[PDB]
Image (cartoon, rainbow, N blue to C red):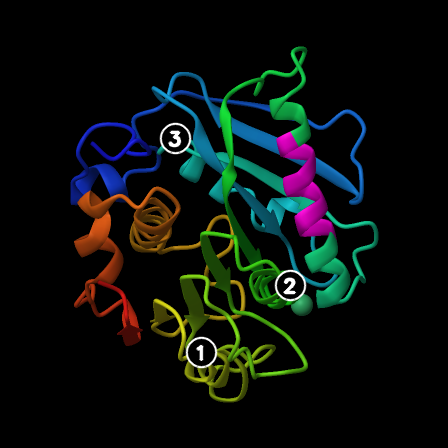
């Protein structure tokens, strides 16, 4: 028995729906430490401790741009913290530091008897996500903290394209027509630079820079893939190996690549 496997056996329909099987509650962090603000989403009875994921927005953006991931992932068995940065103009390195600080506070709250997530988190199992500069920050977080178990940035933005040291399983969401973090000069070179890890590249057909944000028109496919990736690698849950590693074979995807996934 995989001690980290949670919830009923997955189906395409259960992964494509707006929410998974778990009931989700949330709270705003009272005294954020090391970042601007945060909302914690958690499942009320996942059947055991679950991993934690920290999600960071992009330049000038706030929690609303990435908020949909909170309920979506939490409803499948994760504690998710979506954060506002100290300043909306923070750079990827600062975003990475605040992302890790948010994860540290989730771990601290896990040991605080007054917190709603008291005893709900397996603090040894954590992941990182984020949009644009927050996606670049997620990759920096993975490079600097190889104990992280999964990463799934979307339209990542960073001055470098060489993340060759990353050993964390990394799923890159890309948007075909991105004019802010262009695929050919950012997302794809970042993907190609990683030779040590399970990795995946999923490009949304005709998508703009915000193609993976709250309110996007591909929440069924993007949500399915994001949850499947997190489940497969944060929980070592091989029930999700096919969903995580498969080509969707969908006209909504203009480019799909994967390596070392199974
Ligand atoms: Cl950005």
Q: Earlier in the sequence, mark 1 or mark 3?
A: 3
Label 2: element kind: helix
Q: Which residue is mark 3?
A: 75
Label 3: element kind: loop
Q: Is residue 59 above or below residue 16?
A: below
Q: Which residue is mark 2?
A: 137
- Front in this rendered view, residue 141 or 91: 141
Residue 214: x and y in percent read 51, 49
Q: Mark 1 against mark 2, which lies toward the viewer?
A: 1
Taking the magenta stretch, the answer to whether it contains residue 114 is no
Residue 252: x and y in percent read 27, 67
Question: Which label belongs to residue 59?
Answer: none
- Front in this rendered view, residue 23 or 4: 4
Question: Which label belongs to residue 194?
Answer: 1
Magenta residues, dominant SS class: helix
Q: Is residue 246 left or right of residue 44?
A: left
Residue 20: x and y in percent read 31, 32
Find out if the beta carbon at label 1 lies less than 8 Å from the nearest ligand 1 atom. Answer: no
Furthest residue toward top: 114
Q: Mark 2 against mark 3, which lies toward the viewer?
A: 2
Q: Which residues are magenta?
A: 98-107
* Picture quadrant of residue 131: bottom right
Q: Quadrant of the N terminus?
A: top left
Crowd rating for badge 3 (residues with CA inside 10 Å; few <14, some 14–19, many 20+): many
Q: Disc 2, disc 3: CB below 8 Å?
A: no
Task: Determine the residue positioned at 29% across, 26% down.
Answer: 21
Tell me which image quadrant ligand 1 sits in.
bottom right
Crowd rating for badge 2 (residues with CA inside 10 Å; few <14, some 14–19, many 20+): many
Q: Earlier in the sequence, mark 2 or mark 3?
A: 3
Q: Is residue 208 above or below residue 1?
A: below
Residue 228: x and y in percent read 30, 49
């Amino acid at each position: 028995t995989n001690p980290y496997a949670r919830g009923p056996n997955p189906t395409a329909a259960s992964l494509e729906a707006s929410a998974g099987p778990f009931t989700v509650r949330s709270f705003t962090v009272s005294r954020p430490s090391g970042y601007g603000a945060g909302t914690v989403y958690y499942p009320t009875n996942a059947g055991g401790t679950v991993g934690a994921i920290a999600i960071v927005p992009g330049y000038t953006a706030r929690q609303s741009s990435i908020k949909w991931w909170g309920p979506r992932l939490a409803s499948h068995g994760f504690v998710v913290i979506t954060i506002d940065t100290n300043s909306t103009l923070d750079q990827p390195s600062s975003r990475s530091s605040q992302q890790m600080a948010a994860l540290r506070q989730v771990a601290s709250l896990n040991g605080t008897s007054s917190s709603p997530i008291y005893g709900k988190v397996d603090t040894a199992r954590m992941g990182v996500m984020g949009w644009s500069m927050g996606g670049g920050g997620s990759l920096i977080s993975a490079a600097n903290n190889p104990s992280l178990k999964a990463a799934a940035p979307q339209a990542p933005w960073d001055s470098s394209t060489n993340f060759s040291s990353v050993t964390v399983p990394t799923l890159i969401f890309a948007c075909e027509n991105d004019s802010i973090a262009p695929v050919n000069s950012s997302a794809l070179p970042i993907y190609d630079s990683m030779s040590r890890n399970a990795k995946q590249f999923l490009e949304i057909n005709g998508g703009s820079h915000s193609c993976a944000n709250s309110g996007n028109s591909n929440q069924a496919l993007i949500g399915k893939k994001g949850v499947a990736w997190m489940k497969r690698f944060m929980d070592n849950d091989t029930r999700y190996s096919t969903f995580a590693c498969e080509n969707p074979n969908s006209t909504r995807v203009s480019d799909f690549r994967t390596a070392n996934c199974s």
